[PDB]
Image (tube, helix red, strand yellow):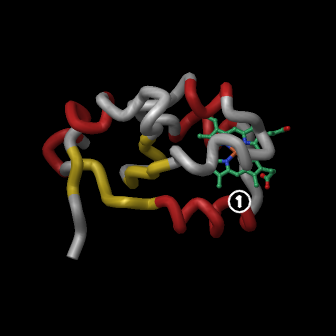
Amino acid sequence: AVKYYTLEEIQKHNNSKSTWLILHYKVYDLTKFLEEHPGGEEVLREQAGGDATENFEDHGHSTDARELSKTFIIGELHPDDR
Ligand code: HEM
């Protein structure tokens, strides 16, 4: 089964309590990863609540980084918002 979230729901997760973002139509909860992120937390907080695909790809992440990201996926962007 797959859980779908709308852009409306996602934008609400951009506070000290929760940090969600979208990458290639998948929704990632990075709340607990902010402080472990090699690239820093500021770069992640600035994209919170929205689609950060271009920025993610812009910094060209390694295979290990991409494999690790999967553990934070909690769902996908609703087809109607794509
Ligand atoms: C949720 C997925 C993410 C994971 C697991 C992750 C993981 C990592 C890891 C492991 C590195 C070290 C280098 C590498 O392996 O590529 C890295 C570096 C970096 N990440 Fe992420 N990252 C994530 C999302 C993002 C996003 C959303 C942005 C920006 C919008 C970002 C910006 C950067 C930057 C600036 C660096 C340093 C690049 C450099 O120094 O040249 N990351 N990330």
Compared to residue 42, the image places residue 73 above or below, namely: below
In the rendered image, residue 56, in percent from the top left (x then y), is placed at 62, 41
In the rendered image, residue 22, in percent from the top left (x then y), is placed at 43, 43
Along the viewing direction, whichever of 5 and 51 lies nearer the viewer: 5
Is 77 on the left or on the right of 24, as rendered? left
Q: Quadrant of the C terminus?
A: top left
For ligand 1, the image quadrant comes to top right
The residue lying at 50 percent from left, 60 percent from top is 72
The image shows a total of numbered marks equal to 1
Compared to residue 51, the image places residue 63 above or below, namely: below
Q: Is the C-beta of the residue carrying label 1 under 8 Å from the nearest atom of ligand 1?
A: yes
Amino acid at the residue labelled 1 = Ala
The residue lying at 51 percent from left, 35 percent from top is 52
Using a 10 Å C-alpha cutoff, classify the residue at mark 1 as few (fewer than 14 neighbours), some (14 to 19) or many (20 or more): few
* Residue 35 picture quarter: top right
Residue furthest to the bottom in view is 1
> Secondary structure under badge 1?
helix
Is 34 on the left or on the right of 36, as rendered? left
The residue lying at 67 percent from left, 26 percent from top is 42
Is 48 on the left or on the right of 10, as rendered? right
* Residue 66 picture quarter: bottom right
Is 70 on the left or on the right of 58, as rendered? left
In the rendered image, residue 62, in percent from the top left (x then y), is placed at 76, 58
The residue lying at 14 percent from left, 44 percent from top is 80
* Residue at which label 1 appears: 65
